[PDB]
Length: 225
Ligand SMILES: [Cl-]
Ligand SMILES: [Mg+2]
Ligand SMILES: [Mg+2]
Image (cartoon, rainbow, N blue to C red):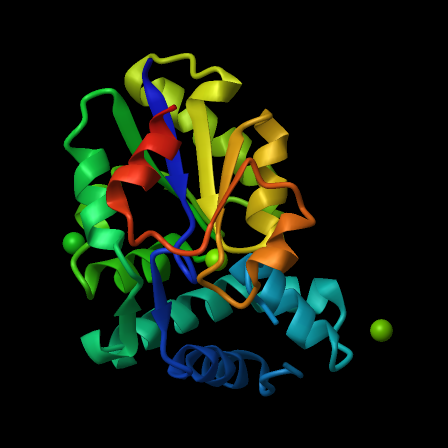
């Protein structure tokens, strides 16, 4: 009965203006001297830092040495520059989150490639951060496939619920979302509101596939059942 529902942010709940890419580039120039070189849909913020820097010849150990400062600089710069007008809430998202959060049998959480501080700043601008009491984030791993385990442990410690696979729902817009759900044999719901079409997403065998979340009642039925 009790259901755990985990949402990706970018291309699932909202989108951000191209300034996001430039905030990162600026933070890396500040810390390492280079923005690297330089799609990152569904990827972990930490893995993106390693990739773009390693592309220009930096060793992993060299990247690691200043990684935390690069992270902090990126977060601070994002919080400084981003405005509400940079964020676009996707179709039906607020309606869906209201429908879920009003149910006692539902626990909502985030499972995202964003660092928590910047991912939650994105959610705060349009005023949907308040729906998400916990999550797993890029602070927790470089590999998205470690996150479901971490989120499951956190949810269980919060509620005392021992969610079974059919009680866990992982929602996102890329193959990486679908793939990380397999870690828990969870129910994956993919939504084709990012850079990948239904035809593309369908090859990864999501449990369910939506075009978008316009029909709140049907998305809810699909999530709870
Ligand atoms: Cl909020
Ligand atoms: Mg996404
Ligand atoms: Mg080398």
